[PDB]
Image (cartoon, grey):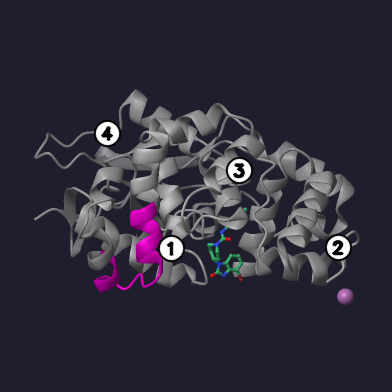
Amino acid sequence: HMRHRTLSSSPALWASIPCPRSELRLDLVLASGQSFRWKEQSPAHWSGVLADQVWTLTQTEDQLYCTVYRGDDSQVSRPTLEELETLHKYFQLDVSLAQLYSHWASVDSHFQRVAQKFQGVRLLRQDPTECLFSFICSSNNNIARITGMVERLCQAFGPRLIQLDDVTYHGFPNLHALAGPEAETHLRKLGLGYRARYVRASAKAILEEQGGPAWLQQLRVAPYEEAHKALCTLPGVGAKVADCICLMALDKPQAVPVDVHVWQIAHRDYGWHPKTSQAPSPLANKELGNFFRNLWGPYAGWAQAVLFSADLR
Ligand SMILES: COc1cc(NC(=O)N2CCC(n3c(=O)[nH]c4c(Br)cccc43)CC2)ccc1C
Ligand code: NI
């Protein structure tokens, strides 16, 4: 009945935000392994679900064009002031990426070279719950396989929002839905494997041990290291997944998620070797995070995303 919108098809239902290409590149950000909920359903048109609503996003050289599908058989219209504020916070456009790029480049010759082609790579401000369970699914996994597990998980547990063409869109499920006695068995049938246990276990833990989603909001205003330790008490959440959530959901820009991916970049592109440590290891991984924080500064996590986006593309 209802189809995916393009800026040419139905320009009446679109709204713009003043945003240069230097500050944001949809094609780089929405497929850099930050969110796993956006798909380029038509060329230069990125469709995904955001806070129990579906969006389609496209851009020019100095404008970010966006349209909303409410889904509750409502009168179709342009995005509101509040819904545009939601998108502004989501891309964290209040922060100048140009000034950060220059600041990182001043102390890093390697970043300077990569910063040429790969501009407008910024960090999304994600829902802690969506981010947490998405990055529990990320362990020893590729972007395409993670995107599969998260899509299936949302269709099975999350509430249906709308159908556009052949794609049925579901919002991310609440903690109670993932904590049920059937949850792990269902999730294994959806192909999560060993990750199915950590999803149910972490959902049950946040509810019983930590007192629901308000905890993840407490970690948002808590300092980085208090938040990191707190997340590491959850089933299937270590330093890597804890740093990812910290960087991408809990506003900890100095959070540098360290696994084999940054290790490769650290060694090949920076000639880094563990100085204080003997032998990858928990101690060596922490040293590597401190190395990048010492080099790039309090937005070290944002810098890593630019090199990550560069290594993926
Ligand atoms: C862009 O900003 C960030 C993204 C992440 N995401 C992440 O670490 N993962 C785990 C592996 C996935 N992945 C993969 O499958 N191959 C990859 C190659 Br090659 C490079 C980087 C990631 C790759 C994507 C989800 C972590 C931190 C930052 C700042
Ligand atoms: Ni070497």
| Residue 129 seen from this side | yes
Q: Earlier in the sequence, mark 1 or mark 2?
A: 1
The quadrant of the rendering that contains the C terminus is bottom right
* Secondary element at image label 4: loop
Residue 209 x %, y %: 41, 39
- Asked where in the image residue 115 lies, by quadrant, the reply is bottom right
Three-letter residue code for mark 3: Lys
Q: Earlier in the sequence, mark 4 or mark 1?
A: 4
Q: Please name the residue that numbered disc 1 is placed on.
A: 137
Residue matched to label 4: 78
Give the residue number, with chain letter if any, for mark 3: 229
Q: Nearer the viewer, mark 4 or mark 1?
A: 1
Q: Which of pointers 2 and 4 indicates the residue nearer the eye?
A: 2
Badge 3 element: helix
Going 51% across and 66% down the picture, which residue do you hit?
Answer: 139
Dominant SS type (magenta):
helix
